[PDB]
Length: 516
Ligand SMILES: COc1ccccc1-c1nccc(COc2ccc3cc2C[C@H](C(=O)O)Oc2ncnc4sc(-c5ccc(F)cc5)c(c24)-c2ccc(c(Cl)c2C)CN(CCN2CCN(C)CC2)C3)n1
Ligand SMILES: OC[C@H]1O[C@H](O[C@H]2[C@H](O)[C@@H](O)[C@@H](O)O[C@@H]2CO)[C@H](O)[C@@H](O)[C@@H]1O
Image 1 (cartoon, helix red, strand yellow):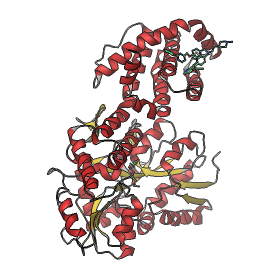
Image 2 (image 1 turned 90 degrees about the horizontal axis):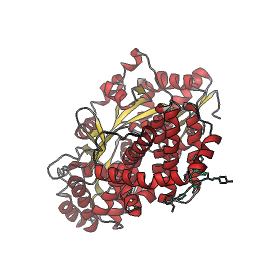
Image 3 (image 1 turned 180 degrees about the horizontal axis):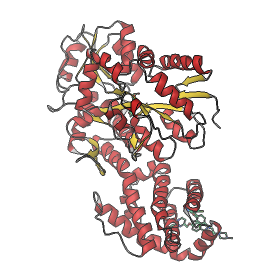
Image 4 (image 1 turned 90 degrees about the vertical axis):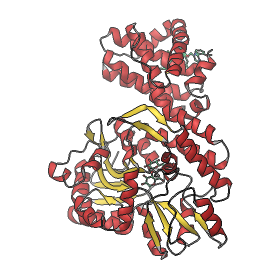
């Protein structure tokens, strides 16, 4: 499917893709291998769709947070650089691209949002978010505004949501508690309510997106913006006398931007893996390769120690690293995609008045917890049905929901299996199962049959009950190790294809209510 003898690269439209194409031309000069750089729209959503069919680019560039989901789906080649190459990059950047103990991408650069201000309009930028309404009123008297930034991508609003205590997945004792989501706590609510109040008081407009905020800052209409290092090139061209500084505090606490490490992963379906490794290690991740990209659109604090020693002297890079140290390195867990979609919907709905801050963040919490809660219920049902004994481990966060959904699932699911016993036994024969490969083919049939019909709790219970019927067969045929991957496969198609409907039902609470 992917053509051998060439390299196709995907990178976001806000990065230095013309600089990257200059590195590709240098590679072609030596090897005769043509390198095509593309920047398709929504490349981070297109990549898992096309790479799953054996298609897509040879190399994908994105911040490290999406890569764990790609790796979990088997879409990325494991990268194994030698120690001499590994030592040329900062160890924390390699940590950002490690998933299940394996390196799944090459780190390129460390990105963090900073406060960018027009020194000619605002010689002393604000230290707090609280003083921005009064500053906006003062600036409005002169035909200017205090601040405009992209309100359509939650990445830009997150530093404010996290400032007073909001968090994505709790991190404590050197580990993430995936069961602990903090998008709907008092801290997140205060941050988002402050943003909504800025919009209600006409200090910001809910429709402001990336282009609008960028045009207004680069034309001197707004005194401040919130953006990353890639934006500096267009501000340079505009000749605005700008500064790059620490984000304002909220309730006396620093804004905490989610820090991304721009990384390059190699498609598992690529027949050009050795060419991609040579391109990335020996052409791109060199002082000259990174300089070519950086001159087009700044990368931020690069992962390559030798080049970073020079960039670190730039006060804009010092400000980027200061904001990064006050924030957090993004997790790379597979549910980051679901978290981002949920928080993106929450900020847009709260900003537009479609939902209150409380309704918006409650839905964001349900969406962010959906995979873990669904896995807990489905995994426990399949394993207790197969072995005849329940899991003694504590249910954890939202244990009441899990326990009640499991009790409901025992009552309804058992009835489904009892009434359709002969029909399920017949289907189990056609799907000849005796090993791990036979479970993977069953999964493919499940995904299509479930995805084809109507969305309702009856069909969801059928999908899970048939999975329990199969897990019983796996226990007797001494293939009990296939049960947990089957539970993960059922959970994945359920949370991915029925995401919106699930959240509208208040997740598993709606299931308990429906069958009450
Ligand atoms: C108010 O409703 C409820 C309330 C409480 C609780 C439940 C409900 C409620 N709701 C909605 C459907 C239901 C019963 O669903 C069954 C139950 C046995 C069957 C077919 C269905 C159809 C149903 C659907 O697509 O709607 O199936 C699924 N729904 C969701 N995910 C899924 S995944 C999935 C599946 C999984 C693995 C696989 F390799 C193939 C398919 C199926 C399914 C599915 C489809 C079809 C068949 C089976 Cl065994 C299954 C389990 C066979 N099929 C036909 C028999 N054949 C015999 C011979 N004859 C000559 C012709 C006829 C029997 N129960
Ligand atoms: O808005 C959610 C979005 O945030 C991050 O995307 C950033 C990206 O890291 C930056 O390099 C730059 O391009 O801006 C993006 C936001 O528009 C996450 O990396 C991404 O996965 C997430 O969807």
